[PDB]
Image (spheres, coloured by chain):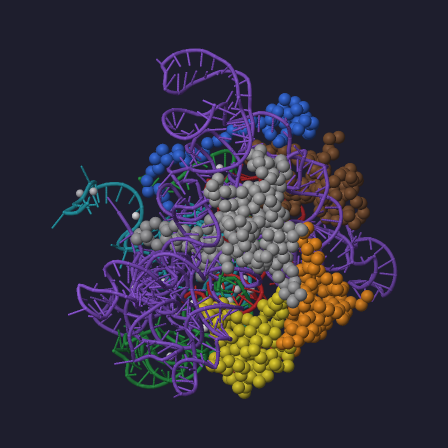
Chain colours: A blue, B orange, C yellow, E brown, F purple, G green, H red, I cyan
Amino acid sequence: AVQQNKPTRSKRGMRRSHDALTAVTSLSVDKTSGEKHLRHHITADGYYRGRKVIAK
Amino acid sequence: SNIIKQLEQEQMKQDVPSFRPGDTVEVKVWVVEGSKKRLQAFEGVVIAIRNRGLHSAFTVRKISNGEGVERVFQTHSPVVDSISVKRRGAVRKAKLYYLRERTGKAARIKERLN
Amino acid sequence: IQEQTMLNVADNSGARRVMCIKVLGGSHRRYAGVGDIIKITIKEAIPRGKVKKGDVLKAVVVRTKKGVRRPDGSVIRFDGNACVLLNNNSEQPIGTRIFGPVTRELRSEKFMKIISLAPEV
Amino acid sequence: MIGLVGKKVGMTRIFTEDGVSIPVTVIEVEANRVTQVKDLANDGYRAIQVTTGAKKANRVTKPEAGHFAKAGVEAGRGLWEFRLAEGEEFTVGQSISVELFADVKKVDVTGTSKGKGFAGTVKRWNFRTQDATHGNSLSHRVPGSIGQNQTPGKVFKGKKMAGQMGNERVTVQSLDVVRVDAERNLLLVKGAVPGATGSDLIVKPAVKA
Amino acid sequence: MRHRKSGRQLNRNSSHRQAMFRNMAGSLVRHEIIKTTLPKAKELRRVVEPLITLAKTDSVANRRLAFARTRDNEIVAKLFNELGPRFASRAGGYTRILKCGFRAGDNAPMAYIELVDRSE
RNA sequence: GAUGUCGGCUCAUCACAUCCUGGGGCUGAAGUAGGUCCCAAGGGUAUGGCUGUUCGCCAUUUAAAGUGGUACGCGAGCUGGGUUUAGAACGUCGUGAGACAGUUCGGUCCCUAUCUGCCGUGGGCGCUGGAGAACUGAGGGGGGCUGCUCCUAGUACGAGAGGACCGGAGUGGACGCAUCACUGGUGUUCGGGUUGUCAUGCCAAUGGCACUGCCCGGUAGCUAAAUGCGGAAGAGAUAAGUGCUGAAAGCAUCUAAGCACGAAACUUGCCCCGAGAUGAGUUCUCCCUGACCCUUUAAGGGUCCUGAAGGAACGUUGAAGACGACGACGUUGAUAGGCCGGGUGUGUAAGCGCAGCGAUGCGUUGAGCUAACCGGUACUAAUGAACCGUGAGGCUUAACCU
RNA sequence: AAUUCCUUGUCGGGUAAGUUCCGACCUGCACGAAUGGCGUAAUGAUGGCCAGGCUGUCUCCACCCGAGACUCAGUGAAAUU
RNA sequence: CACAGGUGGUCAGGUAGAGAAUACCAAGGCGCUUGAGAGAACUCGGGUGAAGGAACUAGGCAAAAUGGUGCCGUAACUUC
RNA sequence: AGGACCGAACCGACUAAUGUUGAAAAAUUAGCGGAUGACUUGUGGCUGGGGGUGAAAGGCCAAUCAAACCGGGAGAUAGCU
Ligand SMILES: [Mg+2]
Ligand SMILES: [Mg+2]
Ligand SMILES: [Mg+2]
Ligand SMILES: [Mg+2]
Ligand SMILES: [Mg+2]
Ligand SMILES: [Mg+2]
Ligand SMILES: [Mg+2]
Ligand SMILES: [Mg+2]
Ligand SMILES: [Mg+2]
Ligand SMILES: [Mg+2]
Ligand SMILES: [Mg+2]
Ligand SMILES: [Mg+2]
Ligand SMILES: [Mg+2]
Ligand SMILES: [Mg+2]
Ligand SMILES: [Mg+2]
Ligand SMILES: [Mg+2]
Ligand SMILES: [Mg+2]
Ligand SMILES: [Mg+2]
Ligand SMILES: [Mg+2]
Ligand SMILES: [Mg+2]
Ligand SMILES: [Mg+2]
Ligand SMILES: [Mg+2]
Ligand SMILES: [Mg+2]
Ligand SMILES: [Mg+2]
Ligand SMILES: [Mg+2]
């Protein structure tokens, strides 16, 4: 099966309407450090919910 | 669950004696008949077995008049009434479906004997 | 029990294997067991007997493998299907004796003649 | 009459002194305090909104507890109407129990549904499987010929063909009642009602004879 | 539909999910920390904890059986002896997860399985 | 500058010149059963043997095995048996190449779907302040089958044989829906037996590989052959038909005036969807009542401060699920995992002891092990934040009002 | 009959029922003796028919294990128009 | 094409086995240059199936089955 | 002994599925036929186009064959599109 007609550039976009991306609804900062880390998991240096796991 | 189980054991009977997949037993159920109510006996050989609380089965091989019969009693059923044990045997298996196609000699199930 | 299906004979005359060429009891009626009427076709018969091979009469299923459960739920199942031949036009058994145990399902006041024979249930 | 909102959690025997085993779904109706009455001059009909459970008083939104507190507050799973007529109930949670279906033998039971989802014919429409063998290329079990041809042109609606199978009211009607044993919010039917345990059911007298 | 079916099949025979988990569990009992896949962890979870639980008790009995799983007759020592009595009081949370996810090649989300008592 | 043939399969949809079932007229209609005509399209409407068949004949069923339209419905859905490629042979015709509206054996069936169309399922925005809900129900769809037995009543009818009506009761066939409690199936995540071989130093005990190696049995879940329930009653207006009273037309007449019955059709009753019903509906509840400027000022545009109800997000997850969606839970916690105890299933572990020359047996032991289960338990993981949404809601008229 | 149009000839056998099959009849549309006639043990991935075993071929599908399908990240076509 | 195809010769360990079959291994060489999840219809390759057992179909197509050594025993017909 | 039997290598190609913008311009998988012989294979050689070769299908003669490929007559001719 093929297209009997060439889809207009217009229609093409309509399809890419829901193709857009999303943001991040803002992330999170740690308490033990201003660690600008992702919500619910390890900071840039072993930290997370306070404390600090994984050396270095 | 919690409501059940208790609502189940609420019907369960305690007249049920010891069992085994090799035992013989002789279940005695009702019959009703025409205007009667006689108790029909059914001495056989347990092959499979219940073990599900109120919900329980027997599965007993007998081999009546020439042909073999198999009955899956429902342990906790008013129709079950009495249920002997007769001869207990050693099997070393949970289900004796293998004891199916056998017949004399090839079926001979060595008694338990404790 | 459905077309074909070779069942033994629980009565005498025209012994051994007999094929069910139809399941009477309505359109599309799939299978039949317990104690239903079945169109049989003697495929063995005995040297003498009363019904010879090739005969196409009717019969009643006396024993099935799918057993027969009753109220309580407990089921009764025999090993090997069996039926009993009987006059075509006006029911009732053709043989005199009935071998093997039967079931209380035939206690119907229309098959009495059979349950009244030695065996069991 | 009106009915009560229960919660599926049954399926168990109940042998009789006669020798019969009766199947049955154990519906649980723990009171149904009417959360609000609906008038025909104020609303437009004759109904009685009720509840049965009681949220953890945490997930209860103010707009929710606002409607409850407005009347006989006491939280609960949700709100359920019950169109009635020629007989009302005390607005505030008058509290109706399983003893309601006392001199009753009808019942309907309206759970959610199954939940197959996957769909696909042969199961959602009880279709027929094509030649398992004897050739047949990539067409063992499939729709096969959905329409007709040029004359028809399109494909008539309703054309059975796969699609989500599950989650949908689907009542039952009838179902002889076994025991209305109250003082434990217990009600037993004949057996086989929709839902899959812990489901919200709407048991009420069968509209049918 | 899997309705109410427990257990994760990752993506391979019921054989792989007996080694890529056995070599992992044993690999966990060693360093007490790992940066595996989130799922490949939440699963590994109910693989070691059971072993540790089984580790609570000694005896050749609950030993050889412990040797059955994890053919490492070495880490079995780490069990019963080391982390054996270590968690000889814990309720079962012998494991942490420490999420982080997102690997290089595959956008796959990694994790950090670790013995609850690893920090020193 | 290609619209794939016949039959089958699968899946249909309509017509009515109706096969069954429902309602009536006439009868060469005693009853039972028929014959024929009128009405009626709700639903239903056979398995095999022979053949490529369609059809047909035959066997045996059924309430019945309807007729026809749909590219003689259906190959970007299946087949490829018939039939038109190339091989080969027979009968036949031709000197022959070859040929046949004769036969015979053999003979490559492509396509990842853009558009309409369907079946499902989300994302926007709109419904005039914003929310969380519960309904109303315009409409739309689903379903609409029928056997036998008994009671009536061995009565009415009939010479007998035979044998009803109306009405009532029970149990089936086929079909649909739901559900795993039962009966079973599956159960490569549970237990066991065992062949070959490799390995863990060896004995013992184990694991790997050989279709899960082969195999026995099985929890949850899912299921049908298992189990429960439904096609109704009742109304409305009728079809054909039947009539009352009734003149035109002194009678007669169902019609012209004028009333009464009347079917599985039709409207509704039963089940489900449903306010995008833009004709966007109703009811209940919840939230926000701080300040300025520029003006092209009847509206705006912008500023600081504020961000509510709620929402979404993230995480633990589900009998929910393709992904979105929907449900539960997030330390004010059982939402998952682990853990504890039980259950279940397997079937009496390992080690030791003893007996036997040994295979092996017995004891410890009914053990050992035990997934999706049940009861319970914060050990682990479910962070405090932050995020979006605001700040009393246009005009005109009427009703009320100080 | 690898030859028969009429043709599913007729009869018999097999089946519950057999336009195929096997044994016959002869009315050979239109067999026939090295473009060989009729037989023939053995052989055949050869044509037809029958049966026992076997079974998901089917009644009527159910579950289960894998590779795709679906989601994410990287690469990135096609016919057609 | 860093293509599941084609390509002649030589060497020939252990256990089991008739064996250059086959299975597990040694020496030796490899995991095939997208992966991570999920656990839908449907397609592909498989495993298990209640009762029936060729009713399938143009046709038993495909499946399922049978399968080893020793011994016993084995029909018509026959070119023996 | 044998164009003998069963069966790997080896030669072949009867069946089905899958592939059909393939892994592949004929394969993969499960079966299948021959397997001391008219066997099978390496290397080199000889037959050349109206000619060769052919256990005979119009088959093969470099993915081409009822007359190969390359170049030329050549802008063949084309009442046709
Ligand atoms: Mg193909
Ligand atoms: Mg049109
Ligand atoms: Mg008409
Ligand atoms: Mg027919
Ligand atoms: Mg036949
Ligand atoms: Mg056509
Ligand atoms: Mg095709
Ligand atoms: Mg053909
Ligand atoms: Mg393996
Ligand atoms: Mg002949
Ligand atoms: Mg000739
Ligand atoms: Mg991508
Ligand atoms: Mg490569
Ligand atoms: Mg079966
Ligand atoms: Mg057939
Ligand atoms: Mg057929
Ligand atoms: Mg075959
Ligand atoms: Mg096979
Ligand atoms: Mg040879
Ligand atoms: Mg091959
Ligand atoms: Mg050979
Ligand atoms: Mg050469
Ligand atoms: Mg060539
Ligand atoms: Mg010239
Ligand atoms: Mg030119």
Residue B92 horizontal/vertical position (percent):
74, 63
Q: Quadrant of residue B83?
A: bottom right
Determine whether A38 is above or below D130 in the image: above
Determine whether C81 is above or below D187 in the image: below
User: In the picture, which quadrant includes the C terminus of chain E?
Assistant: top right
Residue occupying the point 50% across, 59% down: D209
Q: Nearer the viewer, residue B13 or B61?
A: B13
Q: Quadrant of residue D17?
A: bottom right
Q: Nearer the viewer, residue F64 or E77?
A: F64
The answer to whether residue C80 is left or right of residue C26 is right
Residue E92 horizontal/vertical position (percent):
72, 40
Residue occupying the point 56% across, 50% down: D3
Residue occupying the point 53% across, 56% down: D206
Residue F314 horizontal/vertical position (percent):
58, 33
Residue D177 horizontal/vertical position (percent):
59, 58
The answer to whether residue E86 is left or right of residue F113 is right
Tell me if I can see residue C17 in this picture.
no
Determine whether A27 is above or below B86 in the image: above
Residue occupying the point 78% across, 37% down: E86
Question: So how many labels did they put on this image?
Answer: 0
Tell me if I can see residue E42 in this picture.
yes
